[PDB]
Image (cartoon, rainbow, N blue to C red):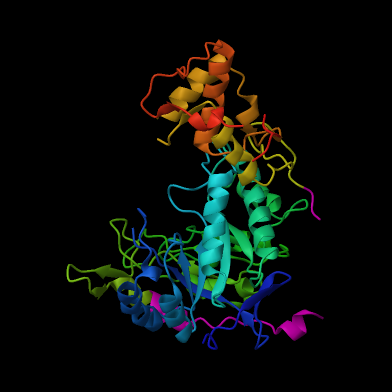
Amino acid sequence: SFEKTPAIKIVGNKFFDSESGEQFFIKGIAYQLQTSYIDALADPKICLRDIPFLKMLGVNTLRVYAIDPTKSHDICMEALSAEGMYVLLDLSEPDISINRENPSWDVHIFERYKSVIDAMSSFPNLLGYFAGNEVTNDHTNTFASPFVKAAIRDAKEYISHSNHRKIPVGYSTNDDAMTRDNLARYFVCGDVKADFYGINMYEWCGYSTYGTSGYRERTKEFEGYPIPVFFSEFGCNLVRPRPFTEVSALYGNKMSSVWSGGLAYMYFEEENEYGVVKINDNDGVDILPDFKNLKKEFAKADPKGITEEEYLTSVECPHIAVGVWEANEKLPETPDRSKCACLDEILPCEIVPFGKYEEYFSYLCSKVDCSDILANGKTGEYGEFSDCSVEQKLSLQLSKLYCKIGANDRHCPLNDKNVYFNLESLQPCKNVFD
């Protein structure tokens, strides 16, 4: 039973408890142990150790960056519900993410997102999904953001055309001044919109103020923004112990009318000095001085919200400007698993997954036309097979060189142990093919 955590819903630019009608404010902390990620919410001994410490801290929300969808989460998710706690969840993992330097929206990443959605959507205390975290981070990689918008669209589509509660799908961004307005506008522009928007906000350092930190200016620029907005991370570590005086500002009357709260970064201490606890060699919890300051600030924080009943009584995309903003409004298409699966059956020359990609793409794309696998977020040109996996794309180009050479001897023209002749290509899915 999840009675202590009714589903939160979005109306306009605010969160609301769907059963009480009261506005929901996030008082959170990031909770991530550093598969090749660790999924503490799949390990009862870890989460049941930490939840009593989370309870003392006074949080109602965790941010989790990676779960293993092949594992069960009901024990930890029920234990969290018992203490009134919700989860914001990233859909990616470290090795399956939109790469900001070479962005793609493809079958491999989309399948990861779906699996996470399938693993976690039955939990009423799943607050929301992040389709991206700081993908575009400065003016040289804004062309990554159309790939993220496509991911939001396709994630929302897949949630929509399914049996699940319509869990909102949003985005988490950094705080680079040259890109931040454009990013905010881009994610609510056109036909595809994020459902909510978190900022990783570290502008308030030590004993700062509302007027000197930048918080006032941020608050004024997000006032009237059409979707819920909050601090997906906060807790600058200039001075230590961290005072967390930003918490008083965040949940004060001025900021609580714009921001839906925030999540401190983070629970575990991990060589970066951001923890509120340290895990000892016994695997027990040692409370750090930060914990008490955060605890005391969250306890004082009493945001003045509005009831849903009371609250009840598309925008232009940024222009393209070279060097500054280069995110095309035209998005890549929904990746097609069945179409890309056909390459595995028909292609003469295949390569098993691996530095070598960049090397082997440079090589093959000098000998054959690679337009069919390129994805360009600046111009909105996406090749026919640009949604396929990193290996299928490479296999296609190698197979193209093989046929162009014409030898027809089953010698694939690239010397590498991962290259092999595909015997399935001699057999008679879809003749739609190339």
The answer to whether 5 is drawn above or below residue 177 in the figure is below
Q: Is residue 190 visible?
A: yes
Q: Observer-nearest residue: 149 or 262?
A: 149
Residue 24: which quarter of the image? bottom right
Residue 6 image offset from top left, x and y in percent? 59, 83
Residue 266 image offset from top left, x and y in percent? 39, 65
Q: Residue at x 57, y 63 (%)?
A: 129
The answer to whether 50 is drawn above or below residue 315 in the figure is below
Q: Observer-nearest residue: 239 or 231?
A: 231
Residue 23 image offset from top left, x and y in percent? 64, 81
The answer to whether 428 is drawn above or below residue 288 in the figure is above
Stretch of the chain drawn in magenta: 294-316
Asked if residue 224 lies left or right of residue 2, the reply is right
Residue 380: which quarter of the image? top right
Q: Is residue 221 visible?
A: no
Question: Does residue 304 show up magenta in the picture?
Answer: yes
